[PDB]
Image: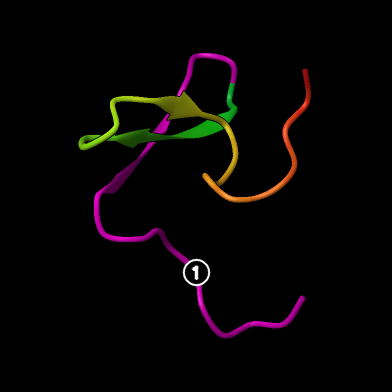
Amino acid sequence: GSSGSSGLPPGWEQRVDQHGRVYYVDHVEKRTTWDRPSGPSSG
């Protein structure tokens, strides 16, 4: 909500697709997600 912190935790990467949807890549978990690893998930 406010400007203070911005980035990702230790072990997660930051990449983007050809569509323009930012997604992180875990090098320890080997998973791809457009949103942070924490939060609600849509089935």
Query: Eyeballing the image, is 19 above or below 37?
Result: above
Q: Is 13 in front, or is 20?
A: 13
Identify the image quadrant of residue 28. Answer: top left
Q: Residues within 10 Å of mark 1 (few under 14, many from 20)?
A: few
Please name the amino acid that badge 1 sits on. Answer: Ser
Q: Residue at x 72, y 82 (%)?
A: 2
Query: Eyeballing the image, is 28 above or below 10?
Result: above
Q: Residue at x 68, y 49 (%)?
A: 39
Q: Which residue is mark 1?
A: 6
Q: Does the stretch in magenta take in 21? A: no
- The quadrant of the rendering that contains the C terminus is top right
Identify the image quadrant of residue 20. Answer: top right
Q: Residue at x 55, y 46 (%)?
A: 36
Q: Is 39 in front, or is 18?
A: 39
- The quadrant of the rendering that contains the N terminus is bottom right
Q: x%, y% of residue 40? A: 75, 42
Q: Residue at x 64, y 82 (%)?
A: 3
Q: Is 42 in front, or is 7?
A: 42
